[PDB]
Each structure stands twice: as C-alpha cells, then as structure tokens.
Image (spheres, coloured by chain):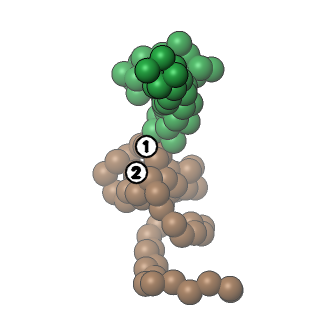
Amino acid sequence: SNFGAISSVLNDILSRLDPPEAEVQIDRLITGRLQSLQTYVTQQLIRA
Amino acid sequence: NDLCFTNVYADSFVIRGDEVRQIAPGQTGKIADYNYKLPDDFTGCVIA
C-alpha cells in the first residue's frame, strides 16, 4: 500500500527524491505501516 | 529577543548570489557538498 506516498518502496523514495522531501514521504509510509500492525495486534487480542 | 541560547556561533564567508540557495539544510551542489554543509536539523538563521 502507498498510504498516499508517491510509492510503497523505501529505496524507490530515497532514489527518486532529496532528503527534506523524501522524509515526508517516508513518514507517511511508516504511519500506514504502524496503523496496520496496530490493527493486527488488536484483532489478535480480541481473538485470544 | 525572548530566548536564551546554550552557545552561539557566527560563521562568515562570500559566495555568488545564485549559490545562496545552497546555504540551507539538506541542499546539495558544490558549496553544500565541498565547502560548507549545514546539518539537516539546523537551528539558527542564515543572513545574506
């Protein structure tokens, strides 16, 4: 998933874009990855 | 005028007008790369 970043590959972002602007793309991507991992553990607590 | 600062440095030099762009965090080009590099988390002011 992109989560509204320009791509879903970290090496692509870092190759494609310069550090001050790569950082906001990475931060958008890790926000969606935290939300999805946090969602998984919440479902696992309810199943447990 | 409201703050206090731990330490303060003043750095001084001459460059061409169109290079002044490079005196900012995360920039690149001959000046930023080989002459004077600001850190990406710079706190301070650039005056020209």
The image shows residue A43 at horizontal and vertical percentages of 51, 20
Residue under the image location 54 percent in, 31 percent down:
A31
Do marks 1 and 2 both belong to one polypeptide chain?
yes
Q: Residue furthest top?
A: A1
Quadrant of the image containing the C terminus of chain A: top left
The reply to whether residue A7 is in sight is no
Residue under the image location 53 percent in, 13 percent down:
A1
Residue under the image location 56 percent in, 50 percent down:
B21
Residue under the image location 62 percent in, 20 percent down:
A4
Residue A19, compared with residue A10, is above or below; it is below
Colour of chain A as rendered: green
The image shows residue B22 at horizontal and vertical percentages of 50, 50
Q: How many labels sit on residues?
A: 2
Q: Which residue is mark 2?
A: B32
Residue B30, compared with residue A25, is above or below; it is below
Q: Secondary structure at mark 1?
A: loop
- Give me the disc on residue A17: none
Q: Which residue is mark 1?
A: B28
Q: Which chain is brown?
A: B
> Label 1 to label 2, Cα distance in Å?
5 Å
Indicate the chain on which mark 1 is placed. Answer: B
Q: Are marks 1 and 2 in contact (CB under 8 Å)?
A: yes
At label 1, the amino acid type is Thr
- Depth order, front residue of A47/A37: A47
A41 vs B35, left or right, is: right
